[PDB]
Length: 109
Image (cartoon, rainbow, N blue to C red; front, side, top):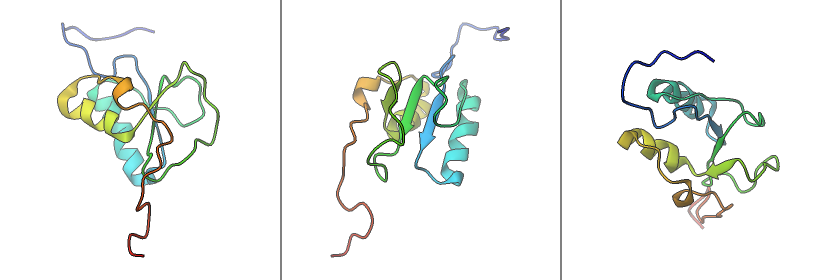
């Protein structure tokens, strides 16, 4: 794979793919294009070619598949932040643990 970067700077997603699962075709798209703008790639869920998996624990409880340990699954924040600070944050800080949060949908009760 031939590259074309003439600089001492590197993107927060350099040679790193990000998969989004849960967000709406709209919210997701935005992320897909973004990844490229920053300096990374984006692939459809399932493709093992993906290195990182960003799942929305807000509306997602369990993954539709059983990924390997190699794949680092994190929350949605991880992706966002990294972009805001333009720096690859630590997955151990956004590691997705099927964390189920309250008020998932209808708050009123």
